Length: 576
Ligand SMILES: OCC1=N[C@H]2[C@@H](O1)O[C@H](CO)[C@@H](O)[C@@H]2O
Ligand SMILES: [Ca+2]
Image 1 (cartoon, rainbow, N blue to C red):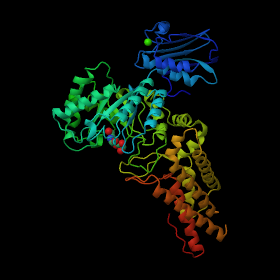
Image 2: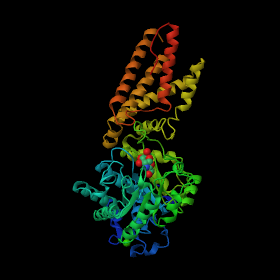
Image 3: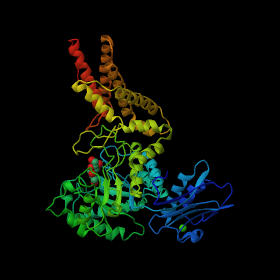
Image 4: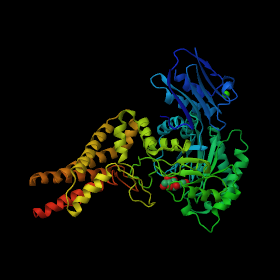
């Protein structure tokens, strides 16, 4: 397994030992970040360098002629790690480290390069911005998965948005950003610093200059990429004319004036089809005026949506360039009581040429976003070979090797968003879903329930329980466990409720009553967790397994308690 999977892979069913004694060619001339990892990883010749370096002159025709491309070869006599550019050589070694198993390598040859030019994460949700340590750890992660873009733009950071966008960061925050930029460079990620001025911007030279001086200050901290965000604002800052003016002005007097500026990106006010006016001008203006080199961000047909051929041809035609995709998943800032831990899917795998970048807007839970981010990295680099389910499992196993089955069990039933203002849904729990649909069917009309379905429901509950208890105590990735703990509790309780509801479906009158009282106590523990964990202004609480598992239990409870209330004439409460 290689994530992301290379564009070209030939494997000989032979395997070389990692060389006990070796000879290093090119250590002094190849990318120092690439060379560090290699030296870290460990007579026989190993050749490392970029195209044009002496060490790799012999393989110069093997090396793909693509930005970030590389050639990698292992066989008995030599090893080659040769990039088309420095980032390519870094990537060559990210692939290398995934092959080295027990101090052994397969004999292979790889020609590799990304299908989409910019691949990464936009930290652009509403809510508590990632902590400093969460960001350090993200950046190492992006580098390993060949993500090359990090767009820093937290809605709730006041030096990024209204009104302190005009002020230089204070010293503590500045020294921190400076460290983020450095770690980004070492992992070969563009740190793109976004600014969001449009809520209170005045279209005068005074504000235009304070913006420039803001950028200038960021440049002094080490930033080499920039963005200007116009999303979700009202007022005079929505003027398309003024926006493109301001972006071209920044282009002409800043990006074009400094030696080493990489990405310059804007995010439009109308940023999805659904919100663009058919007869108004917003998007054709932008397409016509913005200097060709300036990227434009786009979320798809709606604020939350998957990217299709129709969707992206539609946008590319109006902005006269290929859209830079802002994909709003696994972001959950509008369903803050759900975790979105399922697979990444729904995005057309044939349209690499029609996009200039693909970024994911993640959750406010940094570590839990790693499942989707790994997947988005695998997709943006090699969409043609994009495998939904296998990537999801690879992610989990990379993120928590010591309890990967347990993490899969939990994430499998934490995928859906539940009903929401954007109408966007994910599958969840399809494994146990057929058995649940049947078993329920049987009851609400009257016929028998199948013993196989029943045993499976009971096997599910039992596995949910082991997984919850194993995850709570896992110390391999504590930060992930802190994020998900409230949901782990809810999940354990849901499964205990399900085991008790099934026992009601199998006996004698006072057993049924004990179970019924146990269930009511379990309901209340859930209400408790729901009222006191994750109490945020917007969707307070903790919901879990809500697509199939919860409604299954709530209904098998109402029904067995209905049967009872008439076969014994009692008045038991049946709500949930
Ligand atoms: O620019 C794209 C965009 N801006 C908003 C919008 O999409 O919805 C996201 C999810 O609610 C939110 O996190 C983001 O800040
Ligand atoms: Ca070089």
